[PDB]
Image (tube, rainbow over all chains, first blue to last red; front, top):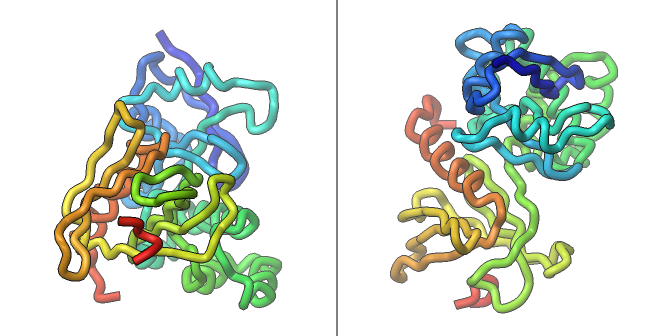
Length: 256
Length: 6
């Protein structure tokens, strides 16, 4: 029993695949990566995401059925699908190693360009230099410079409540470097406080399905480990980021 | 306590 699926790719094209009705997300992802020319190296740097809003996409958990998400959220409007292929990688050095892969470079470039437009990457200072490289279409040079800007390979979540703030909310920001909570109002306006947690201070982490919360336990300075709860709806996505960061840290090949 | 305090 076969069905067609549409999926958005980082360069703005879409692709369609014929997959079995009840396929899981990784089975759909492999089929797509086959249909677009991803080889055995490149395929591990991308994954399936769902568009939530103009400023947030969420990674599909392993036991989801992409076709069910496609059908549920389908409209006539462009792109014609809620599914999208995006980069999945926190260690920007692994990116460099792909600077000779035409497929990878092209996808990295076009998504990085979109992330700059959306404010995730803060070029600002060298905006003009990056614009000239963009206009001459020197993708690798563009990426090599943007890779030094604040916000590259950071995952920003929508603001939400937290059991360890008296009032207001937090915007969670995840990167290979640390785990950052930014203080904001209950409306989402950025206040002026940020806490950085190093990954080495993370003792355990977990989800709370019933309480719609991601949970982490840290041991900072000299005190005793405390649990913090972030009441995010995307708590399984957040847990996957933790597992993935530690995995990339374990297999890191460079002192840089 | 509050993270953004002490």
